[PDB]
Length: 158
Ligand SMILES: [Mg+2]
Ligand SMILES: [Mg+2]
Image (cartoon, rainbow, N blue to C red):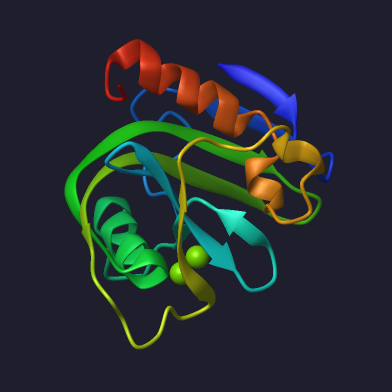
């Protein structure tokens, strides 16, 4: 497993094995690709980030991933695949977040994008994310570059 510190200096433990940290993760993160572009969402408080959020009680992590993509980008998922899992060792709470990769079929218009501004398309990620004020802190640590490198090696992208 990979171990590093996030943007707010909290310890993060990253793994690509099947749910090693928790049997039932309460958070999900979805890396979205629409054609040859990256599908992101603009959080009203955080900024540009890949879709994700909290898992509902009656809902499972896979169903929560599809729901969060639809809510934050208005996108229809063609295929959803589990990539890995990460644990965030916070100051007051420890969270377990599942990473999913989603190939996007289409973007449908919605009346409301909930707690986000809606879908944002990127041909390629800017340089460098860590010091970009328009981006969310969740995109600023090592979770994103390591996950993207694992997507290339698996043959899921390009
Ligand atoms: Mg969310
Ligand atoms: Mg949401």
